[PDB]
Image (cartoon, one colour):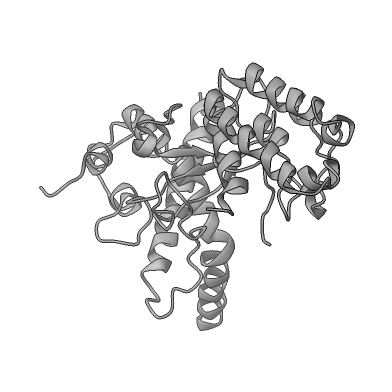
Length: 80
Length: 112
Length: 113
């Protein structure tokens, strides 16, 4: 199963050995971390809109449920 | 007071309190009666419509959804039918640049 | 040991329960202040999701990625970095910080030899 396991475990070791150096290059320059990105602490629940820093991902088809869970009035990349 | 009415109803439609909207429509005809006979479309299409996005109460009624929608829409339609404002009302569009054409029917089928 | 439960799931590396904590959608609104995922758009097939990122990134002491990557002693470690609030975040800094710093460490060390 070198056909199977070895060319899969090489994916297992390589993504880790990349991931070690990236966290090392965070800790290598503690000078000016101005380009850490956080989406700028949008609203969570309450009147406390400035709450905690977030991130963004996107989804696709398969089981079109209805919707009351959202936050906004179907906007886009709302820059204004 | 005297400015809350635009801010009240947009929230009041979102909550779905039916009889509270009946109190909101009660004074709303009186504000038209305070006018001297002014154009009921060209007045209520500034009251039912937000000043910047062009969003009506009706598209606001269909963005949010609760089990009170089937009654909250017809009352906003019957009040739009008892004042000869219906044809301008149901075919309202966004004035806003990002959404020129998100009408009341596209937002209906979106919520399925 | 001074550990949050999210930290405890990482430090022992029990992966499947950590898939639940970082996802955690709660489809209500009397109590959805406990969630960790947020859906923003409701537009049929497309929808923009918001993961929550409190202790995850290395912004405080003893964060999640500091625990996961520097650790020994666990064996399913690559099966944890598939998980979405970690998989894209490593990919984030490789676009903006690391890869541009990486080849400078190559080209400096290359002329050294």
